[PDB]
Length: 278
Length: 15
Ligand SMILES: CCOP(=O)(OCC)C(=Cc1cc(C(C)(C)C)c(O)c(C(C)(C)C)c1)P(=O)(OCC)OCC
Image (cartoon, rainbow over all chains, first blue to last red):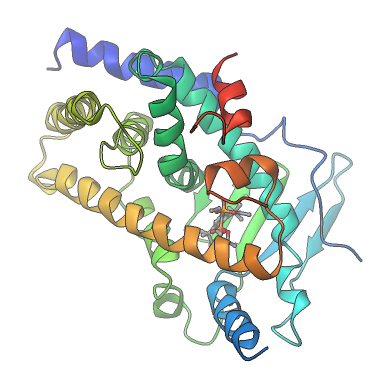
């Protein structure tokens, strides 16, 4: 079994998750919706590539049972490729506030210096957000079911291998296929949050030690709850996915900055989290 | 300087 301490660690994590993860997104409202030179050209060309394969349609199911569906525009002149960014900015900001609250209730996080808490959140915001999004991702329909809101991937010619190209999309399918428990997701969030190698951390020693504790807890949880040889390397697969997610985070953050540079749209909280002066 | 450059985050973490 798990040590008493490990049991307490998981309980605190689950408590935090339940208190700060609005899984039905019932409190997400008041958000925006799409309405109804050489160097510069080079910037735009890269920006178009940064989001041409991350397109989603949006669906809103009203209380009365009506349904609004929004299909994004095809990559044309320019501007139209940013039609959903304001909305996305609102959804992610909503998620980030939930992630900040999550960290705040964790005793291990509170004891850290305020400057370190800030550094850890900046480094892991995107990661924790995507880990939570994975729990509401329906791999059968390629849709993130967020309460009344739904974001569906626009399938193309290729299809599976087509999407598998985008690292973050492949990540969601792969992670979903592991069929993790709430406990494993929350431990993944903790390992990501307490990354000692985030740029700006001062208490490297303490953070590294905390991460290891969380990792050993996850490894142990798996050993105790799934002895089946089929899960022999589950822990290592998870740790490998977290390392990948970290690379994906850096890459999307760069994407954000590139877009921001030619089409500012980040909310105030996003500017702080991803280092945008604005 | 870090807190100075992240007032929102700082505020959210102290409540
Ligand atoms: C650094 C800030 O990142 P970011 O929070 O900003 C959102 C405005 C961000 C969040 C995000 C990313 C994805 C991908 C990556 C899986 C496609 C999503 O599917 C979704 C939804 C909300 C629809 C579930 C949100 P981004 O990847 O969304 C891309 C369309 O943008 C990263 C710049």
